[PDB]
Amino acid sequence: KVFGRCELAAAMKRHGLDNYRGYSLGNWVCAAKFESNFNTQATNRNTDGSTDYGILQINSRWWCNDGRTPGSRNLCNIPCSALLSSDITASVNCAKKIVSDGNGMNAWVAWRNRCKGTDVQAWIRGCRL
Ligand SMILES: [Cl-]
Ligand SMILES: [Cl-]
Ligand SMILES: [Cl-]
Ligand SMILES: [Cl-]
Ligand SMILES: [Cl-]
Ligand SMILES: [Cl-]
Ligand SMILES: [Cl-]
Ligand code: NA
Image (cartoon, rainbow, N blue to C red; front, top):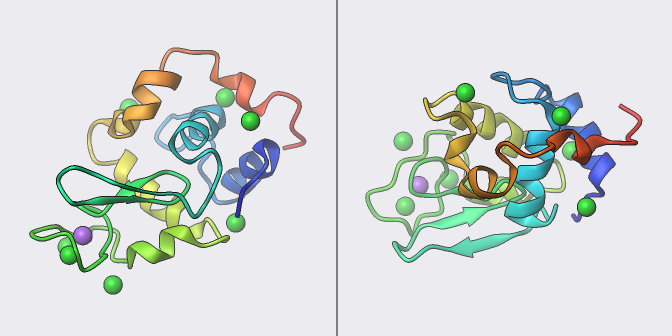
């Protein structure tokens, strides 16, 4: 599924991400825009053989099982395919574990490089929330 901007902001708020670990909703929308262009089916292969999955490009090295990332963990206890659903629940529940891990949203390199310190409230401007 390709979300609209406000549609995704609403879905993320309904699943309890707004101000999760202190990160306002626009931070999560901005991260989704630059990780996936709001496409739940986005995948990207890394040089190390791990793969990033879904709207927040969650990596198989630590967070999900894809059966092709040797020596990896599955800390969200999900198949990586769950992260490609039209239903963002699994992506949201896993992102909550990642952002609690110690480095906050710096875990998302696109958020650090493209969202951090910017006017992220722009990403939810106009939305009925
Ligand atoms: Cl947009
Ligand atoms: Cl915001
Ligand atoms: Cl594996
Ligand atoms: Cl594990
Ligand atoms: Cl699995
Ligand atoms: Cl959803
Ligand atoms: Cl933090
Ligand atoms: Na894994």
